[PDB]
Image (tube, protein in one colour):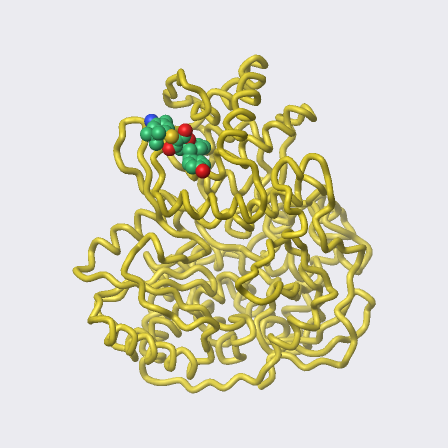
Length: 563
Ligand SMILES: Cc1cc(SC2=C(O)C[C@@](CCc3ccc(O)cc3)(C3CCCC3)OC2=O)c(C(C)(C)C)cc1N
């Protein structure tokens, strides 16, 4: 059927949308080529609409059914529980979209009677009615990127489809526990969101080393959300229902699937009807879990079709990477063509053709790749990294304009061991925090789609617990990694190592002179910038964080917040 049908009504904005990086003394010290940085707006929504709108064709086969049966078996061992209205309310992000029924996120988190009355009513209606399509709002995402000359053009805004706040809270009550525990049980080691960056690296390196002639490849589905059929979404629901659930959770899940996950009318911000969706809703609680289950299922069936030898997968939503035994270059190319044909029949056709890689550092999955460096002792240390272009463009934008979510903070946490996060992100942002005397100010940032409120002063313990003390001492980065970063710096017009080290030494001196937590930041985060290094012993505050739950499941588009 058609993934979308349109009435002609436009996907409209709610407020002014900036498309170009504003000229600003602070972002300019980060990078000078501001014209290279842009933010998508609803102006390009039509472009994205044309691309995501197409007819799906899907044929299933024994390999698909066998894998599905095995997935259901694993699911049958999971017991999940309903979330109380209060537990659900606590997960709502402080600035989540407000309801159209006279109440917003502040109200829900406060448990105002009006918010709760409405939550009860929606829940009650989900139980009584399992058929009326639930309304959804469609908006054009406003994300920042850097121009890609090699691509020929810029990216259009991605689209986000989500239900009313009241429905979102009910989604948490019925499915939060399921989407939190089911995926790892059904997909085992292949479930990507269970790993911290360090653990992902460990899994990837051990897997690669376990093959005799290792070959790896990532599979890019053209518009995965749009390729998800009603069949896929119903198959997902049957896997959820395999869990031991409370009668009410079962009905609510059946209802959300029929009335919302399967499809529904699209309404723009002007209140007009834009059309109808028959594919995955990008902004619901089950988007991450569903996407990973479906990608996993089709890919596993596809590995069998292509007869890949001793393959191992790693899936994160629509992101997929397979590592297997190589059978030769011509044979590997052939194997990948069959694999792609299988995925296409399953309604998961490719964007870029998959291509065989024989070097682990060159395989990019989840926009990342493993790389190597050496800690203080000189020993080799594998770590996760990525091309720093989008992180830096976004850091520039967030410096010039106030952002709800601070991707720069999330990036420092996830890519703490990288030379670019240390040289540029830490130095640039601590300088500004020093300037504004905002080191204590908690900021929102996201990790695996969930929102976290984190205090910059706690970065040393977070990074130590997350990456270990080595993150504060890596040096001798790979020539490839260094080339990639230098290339990016000249493309965006970012200052060089000499300038950043000089800046870091100033920032470090100020931090140290302030004492307290600030001093520890100057000491650990900027030890690289001084000739006479201090010695980084284990920070005692590390052992006490509650860093669990951080790498348990994905929640992109799921409206999740964590205290
Ligand atoms: C501590 C240490 C550092 C070094 S050099 C060095 C780096 O290798 C890493 C790093 C520089 C990485 C870098 C390299 C090239 C660039 O264009 C931009 C950045 C990073 C570290 C954090 C920000 C920049 O900091 C450094 O000073 C060396 C060499 C033998 C390689 C000279 C030995 C030891 N023991």
